[PDB]
Length: 315
Ligand SMILES: Nc1ncnc2c1ncn2[C@@H]1O[C@H](COP(=O)(O)OP(=O)(O)O)[C@@H](O)[C@H]1O
Ligand SMILES: [Ca+2]
Ligand SMILES: [Mg+2]
Ligand code: NA
Image 1 (cartoon, protein in one colour):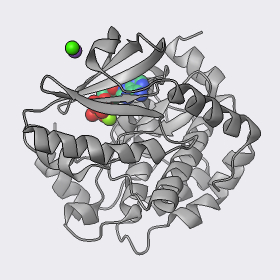
Image 2 (cartoon, rainbow, N blue to C red):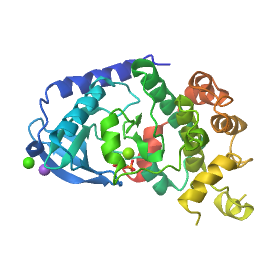
Image 3 (cartoon, rainbow, N blue to C red):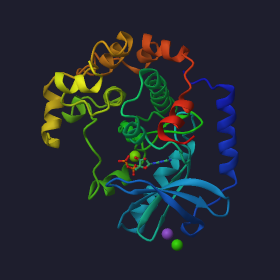
Image 4 (cartoon, rainbow, N blue to C red):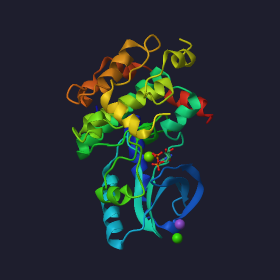
């Protein structure tokens, strides 16, 4: 499931060839083009690396820390230079400058799936089949080639582009950065598995739940917890809870599911197997890769790029 297409292999080759010409990244070599998005951890700008002429996405994490800590962080992120896959956002490098850690990556012109969702209303099942394939393959790559687990799968961490690529980003690789960030920074816990919210099971299975939950949100066009009444559903396909309550709901109530009738039974089964509360019963990456929904989607000739460009107005 990690074999590379001819077009894929060629795209990875080109990326590295370009990266090789870059050299050490420095604050002054960047020119701001526009803001891509934010978060309570840092901001992301579309930038131009003046010397190379390469356009990148630059994430800035404001951190007031000693020269020792930051230098360790920069060291830890170097691991990102080895994560090369068609399902992982490209990495250029990381550096520190005047109170901010910079993480430079390949720019994905389609933005994140949370942004795409906002614009589409809801994402079609066939499109979600391609998204599912990408995410599974991305997690498989991380686990297999780097023994790494994502830890933060969610719609804003899945990026897409006009080329039809779907890639994962923001997977924790620097423990030090996490700590220092844990301060005034804390990302949503709304996509975390019940076991992780219970301090219990902590593995790749947890990322599978997050993916399953993200898929339901995108299919229905709303964070699926708590479930939509019969009233909302009828207006959606014709056919506010506090964060702490949300987390309790997730741990104590049955997992969400897709509405019946409007989605194929294979898609419903796939999300169901991703969302089983008990991590042991929950399907694993190997099983998902051969699930009927994945086999079917993999065989479908879906023009994701075409759909994407028309949906967000690129085109
Ligand atoms: N390589 C990238 N290309 C294009 N947009 C990106 C890229 N990396 C991040 N973004 C955008 O920046 C937004 C903010 O990213 P981030 O700081 O990690 O916060 P969050 O994931 O909580 O949204 C993302 O939601 C996405 O829209
Ligand atoms: Ca400077
Ligand atoms: Mg992110
Ligand atoms: Na600067």
